[PDB]
Image 1: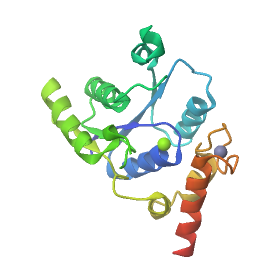
Image 2: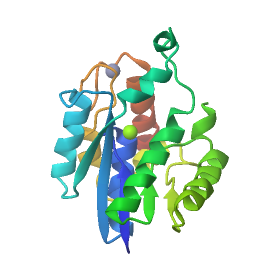
Image 3: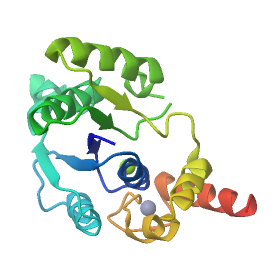
Image 4: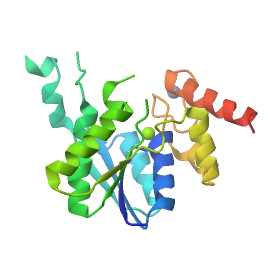
Length: 195
Ligand SMILES: [Mg+2]
Ligand SMILES: [Zn+2]
């Protein structure tokens, strides 16, 4: 029960993490990363969803990161972009006075794997002489288990209706086409059968 910063995006996962963090700590603030798009539906939904439950939100533009993109160095993939996110989130946690850094990451990409988040935690700590603790509450949970959690927090429906998962700005049960939707839906259904 101290101060916590949640890397928030408004998706099923970061939202569940926030709800989670809200019950674990006294103070909880959020951070949303955008690539120069205060107007994006994702950044907006997130700000909405944040309001809905107190918690200050901080926006951060990470478009400078795109300098490292292949095209800019003369493909749009930039490796270890999660290193930077957690790096920044921890610089922020420092200023804002939080010791805890919640994130929805969960092993795919090497910088989403559990050992990387651990090495990263050590690094930020040495970088700033602060006992920072990075929490990855969804690390060993699958989609259906992520719903299961939300539900154990009593926010199943909140999450179901407000978060943005679809790859087309369509809130909740988006297009019902894209991967995201299928994965989110199959997870939901899988959790319902294990009712
Ligand atoms: Mg998310
Ligand atoms: Zn979709």
